[PDB]
Image (cartoon, rainbow, N blue to C red; front, side):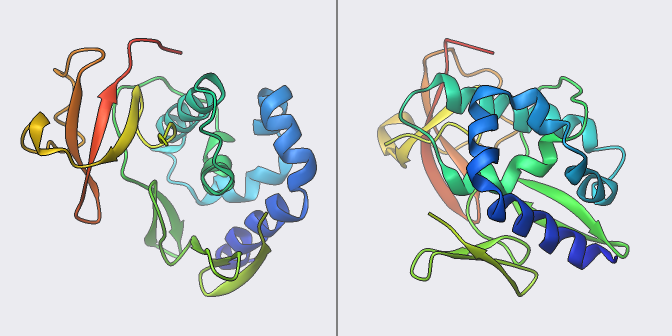
Length: 194
């Protein structure tokens, strides 16, 4: 059972079982993250990264539960397998998350689409490494750790910052961030936390 099909089968599995997954993501997340069905995927994620990725993704998911009206189905399904590792707490922001496929790092972009995770809004279908993975059913809460994405660049808040330059922004302060793929968005550092 090679890596390509491990990635494809993992997302097909989340999709086929989304009814119970979604439920458990709200009502018993720990049990969901510990499901054995995520181990194959986990074996592909670089060992040095598994923990930090999981701490990042679980925090983002908690942001999304806490911040009401920001539930994003596609984002949850994308990031979920990275939550399966035991988390190591850290402060780093990630723009992509790696799965190793035969010595080559495939980069899953935290925001929007990539060869490994490509969602088509017209057909309502997910594609993983060119394989069809099945059908799927104003602030972004699961993109940055301890921030919300507000919307488009607002030039009033000054020149954009990269994702590793955000630590000095004051809590509650707003700023423009180079968020990946050349996109600049307005964000806000949260006062509330998890």
